[PDB]
Image (cartoon, rainbow, N blue to C red):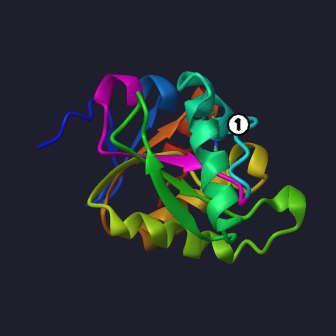
Amino acid sequence: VNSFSGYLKLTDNVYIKNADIVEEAKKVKPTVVVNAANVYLKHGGGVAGALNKATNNAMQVESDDYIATNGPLKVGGSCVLSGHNLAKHCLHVVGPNVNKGEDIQLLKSAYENFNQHEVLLAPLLSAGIFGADPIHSLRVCVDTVRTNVYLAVFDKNLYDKLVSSFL
Ligand SMILES: CN1CCN(c2ncnc3[nH]ccc23)[C@@H](CO)C1
């Protein structure tokens, strides 16, 4: 039993809700919140910009030190950093950005990072400003993640379409 509330159950391990991931994280304080990161951990917009804003830019400060030490992530890769005031940990995961021409096959590799964590609050990878089809992202999530994932979908219209079209 966990404290996630109001989710629709899609499969044995995947749950979904129309919610602002920032507000969900502040309420639940999950062990792991997933960020829709880029390889430079530049949290300018989309989910990343919103999460970073909610940390008063502390996420960005920590991220800049991480990059200065380690260099950029790989597309499809991840790193674990602090969750600041939102969660114990933030798993920064880089899905392919279609608006940069990156290979959508890397979306499965991106979701594989979730399997290193027993329970996560997450957005749909590569959705939103990353330019991928969110219906496809949900399919890859369900077919790749085996740990317990609670998906927050900001857009109510999109949430309804994801549920109604889910196979
Ligand atoms: C795939 N898209 C991208 C972003 N988005 C979010 N989902 C949850 N929390 C969020 N905070 C800022 C954006 C955002 C959904 C659309 O409302 C899904």
From the viewer's perspective, is residue 26 above or below residue 74? above
Q: Nearer the viewer, residue 139 or 76?
A: 76
Q: Nearer the viewer, residue 163 or 121?
A: 121
For badge 1, the amino acid type reads Gly
Report the residue at 62% width, 28% height from top.
57
Residue 108 picture location, percent across and down: 57, 74
Q: What is the tally of numbered marks visible in this picture?
A: 1
Report whether the residue tagged 1 is closer than 8 Å to ligand 1.
yes
Snapshot quadrant of residue 155: top right
Residue 65 picture location, percent across and down: 62, 49
Classify residue 63 as left or right of residue 151: right
Residue 36 on the magenta span: yes
Circle 1 SS class:
helix
Snapshot quadrant of residue 71: bottom right
Residue 63 picture location, percent across and down: 61, 47
Classify residue 145 as left or right of residue 54: left
Report the residue at 49% width, 55% height from top.
166
Residue 103 picture location, percent across and down: 77, 75
Residue on which disc 1 sits: 46
Look at the image and tell me whether residue 143 can be seen. Answer: no
Which quadrant contains ligand 1?
Answer: top right
Classify residue 49 as left or right of residue 137: right
Look at the image and tell me whether residue 100 can be seen. Answer: yes
Classify residue 7 as left or right of residue 79: left
Which residues are drawn in magenta?
25-39
Q: Nearer the viewer, residue 165 or 70?
A: 70
From the viewer's perspective, is residue 111 above or below residue 126? below
User: Can you name the residue that lies furthest to the left here?
Assistant: 1
